[PDB]
Image: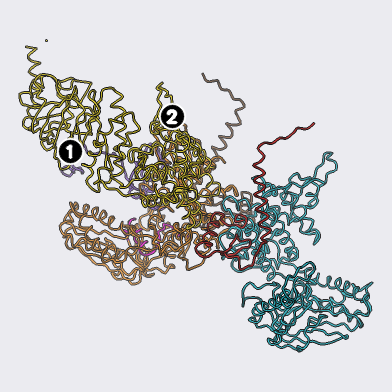
Chain colours: A orange, B cyan, C purple, D yellow, E red, F brown
Amino acid sequence: ENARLSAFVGAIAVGDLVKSTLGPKGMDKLLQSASSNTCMVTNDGATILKSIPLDNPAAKVLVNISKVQDDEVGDGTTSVTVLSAELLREAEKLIDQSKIHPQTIIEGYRLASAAALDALTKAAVDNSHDKTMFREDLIHIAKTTLSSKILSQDKDHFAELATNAILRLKGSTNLEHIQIIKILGGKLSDSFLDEGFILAKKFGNNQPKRIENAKILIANTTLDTDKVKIFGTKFKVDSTAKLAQLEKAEREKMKNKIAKISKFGINTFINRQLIYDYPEQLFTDLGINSIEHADFEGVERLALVTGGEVVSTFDEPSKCKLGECDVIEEIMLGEQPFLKFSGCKAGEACTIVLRGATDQTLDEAERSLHDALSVLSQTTKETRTVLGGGCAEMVMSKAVDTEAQNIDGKKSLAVEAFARALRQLPTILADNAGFDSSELVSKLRSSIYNGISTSGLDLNNGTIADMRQLGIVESYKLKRAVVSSASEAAEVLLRVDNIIRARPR
Amino acid sequence: ENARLSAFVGAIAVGDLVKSTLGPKGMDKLLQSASSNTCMVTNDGATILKSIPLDNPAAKVLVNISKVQDDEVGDGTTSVTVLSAELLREAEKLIDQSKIHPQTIIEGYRLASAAALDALTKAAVDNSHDKTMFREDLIHIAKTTLSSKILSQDKDHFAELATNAILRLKGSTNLEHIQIIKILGGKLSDSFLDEGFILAKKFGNNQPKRIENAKILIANTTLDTDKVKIFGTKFKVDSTAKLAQLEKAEREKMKNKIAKISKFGINTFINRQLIYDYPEQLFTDLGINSIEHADFEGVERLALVTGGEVVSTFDEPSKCKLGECDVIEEIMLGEQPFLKFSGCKAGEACTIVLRGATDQTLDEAERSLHDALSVLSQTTKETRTVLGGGCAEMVMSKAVDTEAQNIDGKKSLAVEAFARALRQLPTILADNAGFDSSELVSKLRSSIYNGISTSGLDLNNGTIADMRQLGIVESYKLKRAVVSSASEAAEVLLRVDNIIRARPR
Amino acid sequence: KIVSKDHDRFAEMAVEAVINVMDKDRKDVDFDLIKMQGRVGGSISDSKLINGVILDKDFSHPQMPKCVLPKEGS
Amino acid sequence: KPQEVRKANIIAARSVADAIRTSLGPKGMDKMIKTSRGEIIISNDGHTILKQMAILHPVARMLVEVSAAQDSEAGDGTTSVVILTGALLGAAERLLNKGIHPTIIADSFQSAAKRSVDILLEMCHKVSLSDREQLVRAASTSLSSKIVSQYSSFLAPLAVDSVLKISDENSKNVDLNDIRLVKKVGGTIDDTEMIDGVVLTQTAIKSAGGPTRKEKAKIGLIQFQISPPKPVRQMDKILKEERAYLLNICKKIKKAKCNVLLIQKSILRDAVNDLALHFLSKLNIMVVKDIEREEIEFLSKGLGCKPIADIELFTEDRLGSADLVEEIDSDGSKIVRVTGIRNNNARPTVSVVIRGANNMIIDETERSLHDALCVIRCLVKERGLIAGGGAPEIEISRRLSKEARSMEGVQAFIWQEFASALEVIPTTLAENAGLNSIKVVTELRSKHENGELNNTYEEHILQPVLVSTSAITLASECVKSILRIDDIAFSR
Amino acid sequence: LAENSGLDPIGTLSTLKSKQLKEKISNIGVDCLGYGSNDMKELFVVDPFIGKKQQILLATQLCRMILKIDNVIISGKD
Amino acid sequence: SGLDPIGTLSTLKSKQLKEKISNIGVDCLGYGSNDMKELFVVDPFIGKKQQILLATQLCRMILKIDNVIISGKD
């Protein structure tokens, strides 16, 4: 039990050190040394935790976790430790009243964290308004990155393709939504923009070049040339022809899995390996298309834009997550076969085709493009804020109460306690600012409980006021960064049942 | 500092002895003496508490609470201390992290108990179904109580008046809703049931005996000749006519009190004392009739049938609780005028007029009628049960959560803390049952939250089942007796800021 | 572990590695024939299945080419 | 008990304030402190007491930083700021018992300090620097606390005329570190030379060949030192190597037209070789060696020059400008003076020279004139003057007591306790003078009702307004930094 | 009485003084029953003048008598 | 897995006798349902066979030693 107490009582005692320092009106702390003449005073939470020597082996783990927030972003480092300490206060009450492995309680935090992120999205605002001023700055910054790069030949043509490849995304900025197709024997000025998912090495011979209402399924199997290495296995046969009969009997059992493919209502099947002529010929009568050379990367990028999933096995027929594309066009350019996928439901993606004169110009253009798009796409999550002043903090609290309706018997207290920790943020801010936490939070939750609540925490008048009129907002990137860091920080301490005392120095 | 611990934590140890003894499967306690050969084993809660000497001076308060509960009914005495212990256990969080005034917490219980009793009433069932057999047996029971009483002369006519005096109430069965009038010069066989609220005295002289569309207002004041004792005063005046000037000045001030009455638009007034001719003569032009000699019950019972208020003062003009009645008829029987009201809005009551031949028959008939009506009124609180097995305990938590929605900041944590103690009753009952209490109570709240209000916990199968099919019910009178006893016991204990040890007798 | 997101990539690496080091006769795998090497930095998506020794080298002087010539169809 | 840890620091802080409280004023009680090294010192100055007290308490050391800024900014009130700091700590003890959070206590001090300044400026008489009769009588009263009295009449215009040249207009903060009091052996108090250009701390070369005087000279700052290398045909071989090394340095000096150069004093090796003085004697280049390391940063500001570490980077633009450079010795001083620098970036930095026979003369005179420059510095940054002795503190407590009803909530009660915390300064002055404590305080509220600032004006007691303003401002930040500490732990 | 009524004793004291100064001169005390604002005069709650005057006279006389005893002499038991 | 060890063990024994002989294990990680055969979760038999042989070999070496002799530290 002391293993958890050292990670709870020991962490809360250390966590309460920087807890009162949250906010500009928070408390302060002095750091005293042995000689006492080297001391200093500061409000930094990360400095106080790292400077104070602690023989507690559980406290040293929290120090390494806080370093991730500084390197990734570097904002709100103190808020991560304060929120992580409040999660331990509720988790300690769940354990002592249970004495069951916390890993089950950890599963309740993952389901509750999903509802908190969805509640912040609907109420989120942005500074993206008047895109006409932001679009003119986006093309100018991209031309600066093109310096020293071979792409500097024509800045207007290359920056225009990157402009329509960002604002038209309307979604995640990850590079997995941008396909890079590069060919040889072409000019850089001939590059064009395409919204389709483009392959090479066209599939099939007698297969048609036009497919309407195509479905996408991901699977891994080898239907051609099984038994890769036959050396070393004892072969006892009366005739030589019986050797090939064993390979046909193994592929004969695949007919049940092939029959389940037609039951899925799909006209196209994707496989990484090849397919023998007999199972491929049956695909024509059943209307099944066989796509080859899907590799791995292109498989993951296709399932995300089409809303599909990837699996190497069949768990049960008529259960899966499938994508679709309306029109598939097969053309040929640059003396190489190409493929084109279009008509995807809610498809959001783009493809930039760069034509180089050699292999050296292709690798330098692809690496320089990712560095230029990463800086431009960084402003999407930057400057975007949400309504602050305890409002959004309470919105995450009432969103967990929705999950508290349908819940398991033993998972209810795990989810319900997560909402109590979210309400500890206005309690700490009210105590550090010199106000009554019990009076403000009580009136704050009753108003935000059902509907039409713009109210928030007002520290000037010492009461609950509307934050939209005062103009109090906080960044949305800071919201997700602290919640995701505090959720992973609490898992590290709970997943450790026994903590061995560290070697004293 | 230690007074709160002895009144809260110290009171828990007293309730811990009766905590595990609740229920047929509950545990037992041991009472051991110095000789140890006189001991015994029993589950009785009242015996264990009275036998063990208690050095805790705050524990003697709960001793008198169990004695009051035993007078009402000999069942549920153990559950009173257990329910009161859960309210004191949660009082620790009401101090440290709450800081809420204790009386405001007690006032929050009155608002929660009001919704808890109303929630149990709608969900209460009874064996009164097929009232044809139930209503017929009511007159036969009343005839058995007529033994040794002068009412035994005629069983059919006298018991019929007592039967209709109960079911026709449609409300509280207490004798405060029944009026008894003792008169002379008649026979007991001529008595009949009349709801017209007959009283002895008359009112008015030249005023008519019939009033249509009457407005009744109840107030208590002396408008005629205050300071009834004139002995000892000294009147210093220059002339005899100047002495009457002070009395005439009071008559001019009477218009201020009459103006507030005239603005209410009432033709009927209620006064306990008399009224001088001048303020009574002004009521003739306004058509205001004043009733005199209303005693005490006549003041309270008039506000119950007419929907009035018992306050004697006006806190603001044109705001008050007003009643009304269709027709006020004045008749004369037995050489005395009677007052029979007619057309009272939502009036529910009955008045049994006992007409005797002497004073000895009036006192014996009134005392015998109260004993006969007590048996009929007992059938309303007897045999009427509610769904048990965690059902009724969880339903009360839903009504508390309704009040917990709209609440101020001080009582927000007080009302919410009361809902936690309601779920502790099925938790403790599931402790000694050998099953998991945390899983059964959790799944019970989510089921009743949306629909399915009749569900409960099954002790045999350890799951949620229909209480109507299993046939497990608990008396409704027991539910109100425990809540009323716990509300009065916790009202005194929470107000305790210090402990004064009682003097040993 | 977080690796469970990319697990589909690491699944195909162990299929071809065991077949080469193990023969169907004895059906045994030697621990000395499996070189386990890792470094700090990068990501888990860049892991590739190599059929031979890594032997990290900077090629000494930078003038040396990054590829080995066939030496006239040798 | 997170607050009880802070309450233990508040009680320990009030014990230090009560010890300094007895030392307020010239009639205050002195404190005897015996250092661990065996040195025995005593004085009534609160800044010197807390400096050698060696306080090991973490919170109590905040008074040392405030007392250091009190003398650096205002220059007066280092003792009174400690009493005012302890007054708010004593009143905060009753505030914690009522359930008041220190944030409201700390935030109310910001509004209370800014309000006390605006009230004080209304009763203060605004004065201008154009009137020289007010500055003479202001600095003359500060010299009445020292043994020198009749000879202090000539020192009054000395400090006034030095500030008026560098005052200009809208100068805001004026650093007095550029004004240095030169202490030399010999002379008298009545003998003083302003030398507005600059004054060094060292003499000139007494050897043969030194010109000791030059007309139209450029004085640079060179941290280097000309010495033979210090990491028997053999005799002449060493001389040819040493003379060539000493000449190569002098070759770039002639091409740079350097009349006067400086050499940093180094006790390790030799400063300037005797052969180097004879080499530059033919070139008519004055040499001044043994320059103190403390004056290196001083000369880098008033002269507008920059230090030259290496001869390779030495240029002409880093030199100075001097019209005439001569050595004038009244008696025994042998000091070099410079006049008419006329630098655009640099300003007229004036160094006051003080002459005296006994050691106790130039010492007590230095501390007396240093406080006189601080009082004049207060009038430059903030105009106006008030009567000292706790007179304005009585009326401020009266106005804030009536205006406390205009507020609402918990903050309204703080204004009532803040008015009582300002009455400790005039009460201590009445206690240390032997007069009855409560009797004199009652006479202050009685007389200040009818009259306004009316007698210390006849007694020539004038306290600058910036001292009373900075005393409240620094105390508001000092008490705030105390209550904001809720705990302390070992950190190393 | 403000602490026994569940109100801020310092905030209520400053509130009662502000309502009796800038608005108008009246008598508004601490609320014995739960309400939302000041001006209990509407409830017609009155106290006797001779009763309140007798309290301040005995409290003043008691404070004077306590200051007149500077020593506590308690004899032992036999 | 956070479940009743006795209540779960009685369930696995009842499904393999009255219903039919099959393999149904305890799920440590949350899955869809029981009957891992539907999820195609397989474990090596010789791998589990090597565990029960080393377990009996380790249990014997513990019981075969009735004496504990050790010297001191200098």
Q: Point out residue C29 in the picture as x, y percentages from the top left corner.
A: 41, 40
Magenta-span inclusion, residue A125: no
Q: Point out residue B408 in the picture as x, y percentages from the top left corner.
A: 56, 62
Q: Amino acid at mark 1?
A: Gly
- For disc 1, the marked residue is D304
The 10 Å Cα crowd at callout 2, few under 14, some 14 to 19, many 20 or more, is some
Highlighted magenta segment, given as a residue range:
A292-315
- For disc 2, the marked residue is D30
Quadrant of the frame with the C terminus of chain A: top left
Image height check: is A3 above or below D337?
below
- Whether residue E40 appears in this view of the structure is yes
> Disc 2 or disc 1, which is closer to the eye?
2
In the image: residue D105, left or right of residue E38: left
- Chain holding disc 1: D
Of all residues, the one furthest to the front in this rendering is B238
- The residue closer to the viewer here, A212 or A152, is A152
Q: Secondary structure at mark 2?
A: loop
Of all residues, the one furthest to the top in this rendering is D232
